[PDB]
Image 1 (cartoon, each protein chain N blue to C red):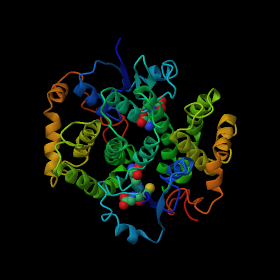
Image 2: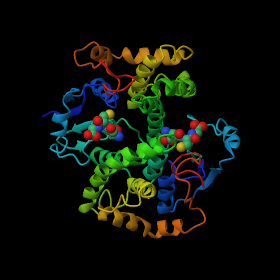
Image 3: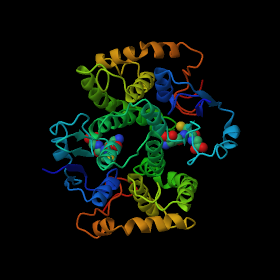
Length: 214
Length: 214
Ligand SMILES: N[C@@H](CCC(=O)N[C@@H](CS)C(=O)NCC(=O)O)C(=O)O
Ligand SMILES: N[C@@H](CCC(=O)N[C@@H](CS)C(=O)NCC(=O)O)C(=O)O
């Protein structure tokens, strides 16, 4: 009938996936759990019949998946995006992980009581990671060349998130600033960001010291 | 000539990969950085010509990879282990991530000043995660059935590590205890664990409050 994507009504681990979906113009319904609906989730966690109960979850009627990275890869795999040979598939997983180093580096410290200080540490390292992507892009339109791949959306999500921790972390990385704008210009993405379905905030769980609240 | 696998002379993010290598009986040399050799690494970090300088790194002469998960997947991809169709490839990435929830859950708290207290929290949740694997195994010899897949080694590494945090976390999970023993009985793995190449300790960086030291 139509695949279902379940997660908290926040950006978190699933935002890049939503972006990929719209880009592919894939049909999908959403199970959005509000901050006061942990009971509704705890009442459904073991009912869906998922192998490893967790959020997010993607039910395809053909499958019952639960790891965010397995879900994003599965979707792209359906559209033959992921590789073509070991070497290319590896290149794409390398991009994946390097963005995760940034995205996860934020999730780690966010939520913590010492966030305000840990922030200093993470931000002092951010430039070295950003640089790797800035160079990559110096001779490629997208992360993997002329064509889009799911890591492009992962990187976009990461960029969106760090700009909130520090509005200036991109000054010094013009290629990254263009890339952020180029992704937003994709007809499908432009349409999505201006739509009712776009979850602009929060970045993390509503409880996080960073990216939380409303 | 022969692929090179570079990393700190510890288990860390690369142990499951070493296990996979031996299992496949793949030829490979190692660049092992000792705790007093950060200079040697900082002097090589930008020389290898890797796209995203980091540890671990896998140089195939055919490729220059750096994300631990991209490296383990690449190796198995060379041996046609990873899938056969989207659905199977997804199932295998789901297993990946679920083990990482355990392995990374340890790395997160290890290294911290509050480790001793965070330990209580992580251990109180460990059972729920362990249970998912115990059930999976109730009707399958390995994680993906009758045949081995790289997540099997990831899970073995995870098991090895938690048994140090709490020697009793496996009491109550007999299938998991057998699985741990079954992996150790693979001719290739048995041979490796008894060899000079096996890095038994440390689990994390020598600095970690947990898994560190000598
Ligand atoms: N490694 C998993 C982690 C998932 C996860 O931690 N999800 C959180 C939200 S970001 C959820 O609250 N877990 C629900 C649960 O464990 O019941 C993934 O990549 O999906
Ligand atoms: N997400 C990366 C992280 C790698 C990483 O953090 N490696 C640590 C050791 S566990 C190393 O010290 N990094 C070396 C560096 O950043 O120069 C991966 O999966 O490989």
